[PDB]
Image 1 (cartoon, helix red, strand yellow):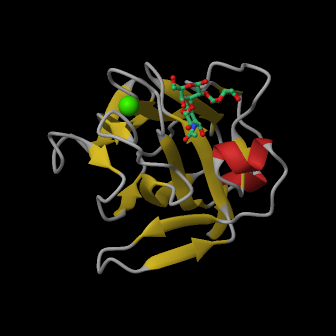
Image 2 (spheres, rainbow, N blue to C red):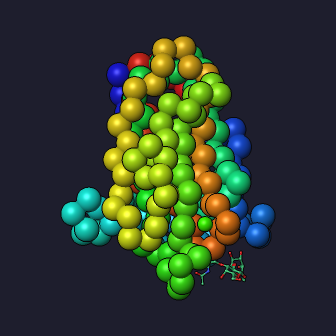
Length: 171
Ligand SMILES: CC(=O)N[C@H]1[C@@H](O[C@H]2[C@@H](O)[C@@H](CO)O[C@@H](O)[C@@H]2O[C@@H]2O[C@@H](C)[C@@H](O)[C@@H](O)[C@@H]2O)O[C@H](CO)[C@H](O)[C@@H]1O
Ligand SMILES: [Ca+2]
C-alpha cells in the first residue's frame, strides 16, 4: 500500500457554506485565506492545546452540509486519516461564530465516522483537534466528507488537516 493526500487527488464535487460561490474549497490552505491567495498554512489546536501547522489538507466552510466527494472505486482504499477541527485563522468574534454541529465521513451512503458520538454539542474554535484514523470497507466506491454548520456558517472554517488515504491500488 501507499499513502496519498486527499489534496493530491481531484474530488468529484466540493460544496461549501460560504455565500460567495465563486470561492472554492481549498487544497492545502484554510478556506478564507486560501481564496485570498495567502500563504497561510492550515493550523489546528492539538489535543494538548498547542497549535500545529500542516502542509497538506483541505479547507472548507461548513454548510447544510458542505460535502466533498471522492470517487474511490477500484483504488483499494483501506484507511483514511485526518485531523478535524476549526482552523486557527477563524475569528471567534462571538458565540455564533466557529460552531460546527458535526463532521461525518460517509462511504457509499453509510456514516462510518461522526464527531457526534464524542462531541454531541459539536465543535468550537477551542475544541482540540480530533484524530480520525479509520478503516475503509473493501470495494468502496464513494467517500464523502460532510461538515454541518448548524444555525449559521459564520467562522466555520473547517479543515481536514493531513488528510490522506492509504490505498493498495490506483485512483
Ligand atoms: C471576519 C470573519 O471572520 N468573516 C467570516 C464570516 O463571514 C461572514 C460574516 O462575518 C457575516 C456576518 O453577518 O457577514 C458576511 O458578510 C461574512 O462573509 C464574508 O465576507 C463577505 C464580504 C464575503 O467575502 C464572504 O464571502 C465572506 O464569507 O464567515 C464566513 C463563512 O460564512 C467566513 O468564515 C469569513 O472568514
Ligand atoms: Ca456554525
